[PDB]
Image 1 (tube, helix red, strand yellow):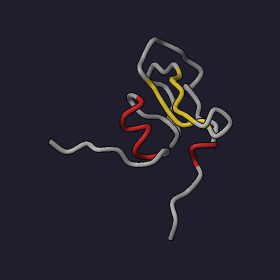
Image 2 (cartoon, one colour):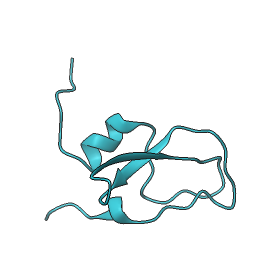
Image 3 (cartoon, one colour):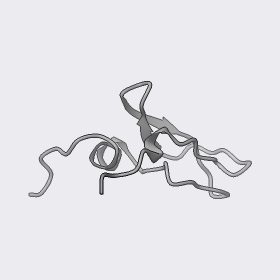
Image 4 (spheres, rainbow, N blue to C red):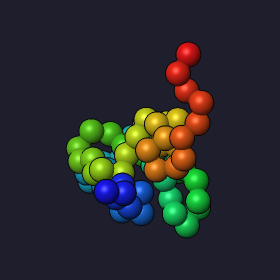
Length: 65
């Protein structure tokens, strides 16, 4: 019943940091935001780009063919 609001949740890199296309939605920004990740931690809020980040936290767009 209705999705969660993890988009507001605060993820964790895992005491690390490295250039990686990690992306998630920010309510204050009302859009997606890219964050840095390496491979130590990782919370629910964490995608690979604005695409998967827009269909999971934002609305749905035309993506099939």
